[PDB]
Length: 217
Length: 217
Ligand SMILES: [Cl-]
Ligand SMILES: [Cl-]
Ligand SMILES: [Cl-]
Ligand SMILES: [Cl-]
Ligand SMILES: [Cl-]
Ligand SMILES: [Cl-]
Ligand SMILES: [Cl-]
Ligand SMILES: [Cl-]
Ligand SMILES: [Cl-]
Ligand SMILES: [Cl-]
Ligand SMILES: [Cl-]
Ligand SMILES: [Cl-]
Ligand SMILES: [Cl-]
Image (cartoon, rainbow over all chains, first blue to last red; front, side, top):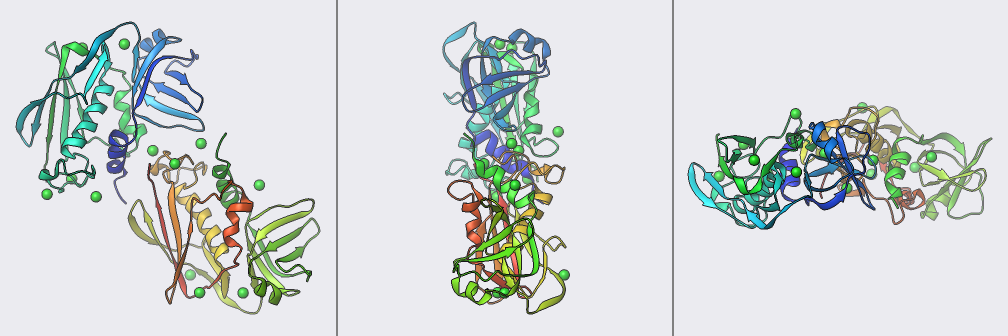
């Protein structure tokens, strides 16, 4: 009856704790499309369509960041999220953001959207960004504060917004974008998180974000 | 270590065959809190905290319905489950159900939740209901079909749900409820089935069910 994608976007992007593993050794299985990181409670399984990258990462110490969802028994899944552990930046870089809210542009940078990775996954930046947008603009509704109240509750999220895009602007002239309100075919994380299966990375010092949020009735 | 309550709720409510005995004579023991029904393989022992009811039932022909669990040697236990054999309905009555799934209400009646007893145990209705909810909504996970796939697998049951209630609405009214995810203190049937020890009955023609299933992390 309902759209499970609404609660799932809000939960998985803004309430559930992100995966944040540093310098963890992959288990080096024969599985071509997965890396696997074991701990005392569960195994985290990363899936990617970049088999060549994953082959190179087999048995290496790696960083993992993003959104996980439940697997059978003591397993959890994440799409991509994996980076190498060869070099880092000397400190956290806050990613510069150009943001348009109902067509009105401003700029912001925040400790809440930052990385010290030399190459960071687009996933890590995106999930941090959406958590921040929920905090500041209540984009998915029910953020639990008064921040973003000025935009109303007209959308099916009980928010002011139902259209939005994050655009990664590379030093290039290249870009790529994700839809902030994409719920996949069924509103389930196995579907909507699949956008991260390329394990796309960006050079952290050499990109910025353009963000757009709006409403259409 | 795991939560044995997960597998036990799934097994005892949805895989293990329910006790369904009709017009069986109690053995008329001196035991105040138990009735006993003997067959060629084992004795089924019903336990209740309603000593007055059990005293009245001693040595009578009775109906027994619910969930049994293992006793020593050739014995099995059930909490309550016992009704008299004086009168019945002319055919089975499907119990009307109001159900909320993630806050969305609909109505259903089904042959799978029905009784022809004039007074039926809340136990019989509850266990039938939960088997039906597993079939239709995969509430306890691993139902073995695609029904309920649309709710996902985020919960520790590998299902879309971790909060739920069945409410018996009497026509007076008077309600009482059971928690659909209660596992008792230890996850064992001797514990979680104890909710049925009152041998509570309802007048079958004069009640309906309100059911609520949802998820929180
Ligand atoms: Cl499981
Ligand atoms: Cl990398
Ligand atoms: Cl509004
Ligand atoms: Cl909307
Ligand atoms: Cl709402
Ligand atoms: Cl999809
Ligand atoms: Cl780049
Ligand atoms: Cl069993
Ligand atoms: Cl009775
Ligand atoms: Cl009917
Ligand atoms: Cl899910
Ligand atoms: Cl859970
Ligand atoms: Cl009643």
